[PDB]
Amino acid sequence: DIEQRVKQAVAEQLGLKAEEIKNEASFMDDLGADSLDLVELVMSFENDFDITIPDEDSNEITTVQSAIDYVTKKLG
Image 1: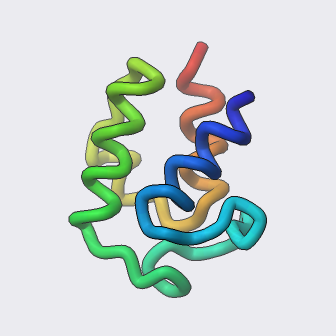
Image 2: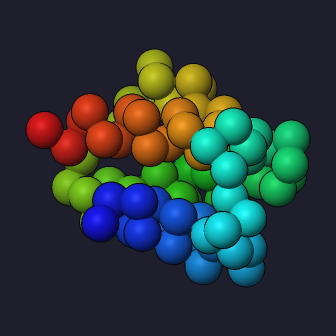
C-alpha cells in the first residue's frame, strides 16, 4: 500500500484529498506548498520509509509523481 501511504501523507498533512491528488499535480504550482511542507513532508518520508533524500534529487521533486517515482525506486 505505497499509494495509500504517499497520498494519505500529502492529503493529511495539507488537508487535501487523496483522490484530488494527481500524479501530474505540481506541489508548489497547485497546492502552493513551500519548503516548510516539502522539507517536512520529505522529513516524514524519511522516518516512515526509512530512506534518505538528498537535496541533489530534492530539488527535482516538483510533482506528486516525483515523490512516488523517486521513493518507489528508493524503497529497494
